[PDB]
Amino acid sequence: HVEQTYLMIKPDGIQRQVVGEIISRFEKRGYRIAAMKLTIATPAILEEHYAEHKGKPFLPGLIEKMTGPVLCMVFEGVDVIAQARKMMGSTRPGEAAPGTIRADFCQQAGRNLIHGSDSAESAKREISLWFKPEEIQSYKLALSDYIFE
Amino acid sequence: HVEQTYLMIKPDGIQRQVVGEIISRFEKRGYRIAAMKLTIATPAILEEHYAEHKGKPFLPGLIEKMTGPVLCMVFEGVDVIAQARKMMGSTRPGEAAPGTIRADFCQQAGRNLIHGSDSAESAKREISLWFKPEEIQSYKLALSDYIFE
Amino acid sequence: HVEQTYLMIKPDGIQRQVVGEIISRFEKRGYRIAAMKLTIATPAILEEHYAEHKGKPFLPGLIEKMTGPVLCMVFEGVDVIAQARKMMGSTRPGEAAPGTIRADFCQQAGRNLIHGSDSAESAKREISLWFKPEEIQSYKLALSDYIFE
Ligand SMILES: Nc1ncnc2c1ncn2[C@@H]1O[C@H](COP(=O)(O)O)[C@@H](O)[C@H]1O
Ligand SMILES: Nc1ncnc2c1ncn2[C@@H]1O[C@H](COP(=O)(O)O)[C@@H](O)[C@H]1O
Ligand SMILES: Nc1ncnc2c1ncn2[C@@H]1O[C@H](COP(=O)(O)O)[C@@H](O)[C@H]1O
Ligand SMILES: Nc1ncnc2c1ncn2[C@@H]1O[C@H](COP(=O)(O)O)[C@@H](O)[C@H]1O
């Protein structure tokens, strides 16, 4: 039983030129790239991405920081929603565990490199927001017998 | 002072072609390769290796997954039995700590890349099962003065 | 918002030829190299470095192990004193978390690769002991807008 999560490299990941290193961390566990697209995020889409925070005082500055190039991604694997969050580490890099993306690359929450869905419901919503169904690619990894039980 | 542990790269580690990366993680700590042999594990030797699980429902499928090429290894170092277990991480990759082999490479317990002895008693038994005493090589690391206090 | 910490690669780090790997771990978080100097540590400077331990029975052996080439470093970043300690890991490599320098490279406390300041007061004192003010370089990282919130 696999699932799919939405992972997005934020503008700091693009500008620091660590896109490949980020992708390699997820590929290393045998997670499958199901979708990938470079875009420039707009306020219109970011308002919906961050809909839970409508009306909050930090939302304008958060949208501003995110208005830039991003890499939209979908990865598939067992428990991948929760596992991707564990791999990213805590929101605040200073609190994240060594070995996580945020602890290894970052200093502050406002520049923490990557977003990932926080739940099954959020993953479905975010994938549908950033990708049309025709952009989601279904194929089987050739090493499946050595990745899955 | 130093101990020796039995570590075995499972068929998934061979087939995913991460043998060198695994070895490098142990070399990086100054652990000494005391023995190393590629073989193909067979049901008869695997039944001995997993003797504690004789008759349990999972054992046939476990033996099937393990019937394939494996890299038998003995590493030497301070506290290396417990330390190698810590470096492998939890049996279930989803529970293993960031930075461990199983967290960094794997998804499920049935394909968790590597075996390591769980105790001094098990290390003695496993080394005797998979190696002849004379495949264990005695030599000293030239960097010993900078590895050991 | 940023502070500076004193980090010193010990003779084992020099002799095992992992200096670049150590530096890369700190650069990876966008920490700025403010000072760097190769020297050979001598007993008289080490007595001042370890002044808090005057009279303790372990001090002579400690000074002996530390007599050798060292790389003196100052890194700057948000919370970098505490964060560098977290990245080094526990004094004893066998207790340190996977993903930390000491867990990834070392076996014993007496050969644990690196020193880092333990507090704001120790950072100020150690920086002044090992570096003259003219050796501390002030410049801005070009990627600052993507490192700092
Ligand atoms: N500037 C901020 N202030 C408060 N909370 C934030 C801020 N930025 C991000 N968050 C929280 O962290 C979560 C993940 O944000 P993101 O990684 O940008 O998707 C959001 O859903 C917020 O709950
Ligand atoms: N399929 C399984 N079912 C139950 N326990 C298992 C299974 N695979 C591994 N284990 C446990 O994990 C330990 C180490 O297994 P291995 O790494 O395959 O030698 C065994 O000694 C078992 O206790
Ligand atoms: N170079 C060393 N050799 C042996 N033991 C040490 C050394 N440095 C620190 N320790 C001890 O290791 C233990 C753990 O250190 P810490 O985690 O820093 O409290 C303490 O009890 C220290 O006294
Ligand atoms: N041989 C030792 N015995 C006990 N404690 C030690 C020893 N070496 C270092 N320590 C402790 O660990 C701290 C960090 O040591 P260092 O990394 O050498 O600066 C020292 O300030 C001591 O508190």
Image (cartoon, coloured by chain):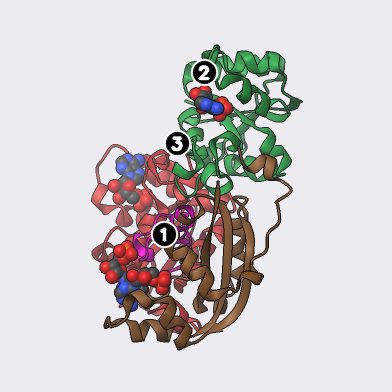
Chain colours: A green, B red, C brown
Quarter occupied by residue B58: top left
Percent across and percent down for residue A103 are 51, 46
* Residue A70 shows in this picture: yes
Is residue C103 found inside the magenta-colored segment of the image? yes
Identified at 40% across, 78% down, the residue is B148
Identified at 67% across, 21% down, the residue is A136
Does dot 2 land on a helix, a strand or a loop? helix
Percent across and percent down for residue C75 are 58, 60
1 vs 3, front mark? 1
Chain at tag 1: C
Residue picked out by circle 1:
C119
Identified at 52% across, 52% down, the residue is B13
- Residue furthest toward the front? C133
Which amino acid type corresponds to the residue marked 2 in the rendered image? Answer: Ser
Identified at 65% across, 32% down, the residue is A10
Image: magenta residue range: C82-107
Percent across and percent down for residue C106 are 44, 68
CA gap, disc 2 and disc 1: 41 Å
Does dot 3 land on a helix, a strand or a loop? loop
How many neighbours does mark 1 have within 10 angstroms: few (below 14), some (14-19), or many (20 or more)? some
Residue picked out by circle 2:
A122
Which amino acid type corresponds to the residue marked 1 in the rendered image? Answer: Ser
Which amino acid type corresponds to the residue marked 3 in the rendered image? Answer: Glu
Quarter occupied by residue B45: bottom left
CA gap, disc 3 and disc 2: 27 Å
Count of numbered tags: 3
Residue picked out by circle 3:
A149
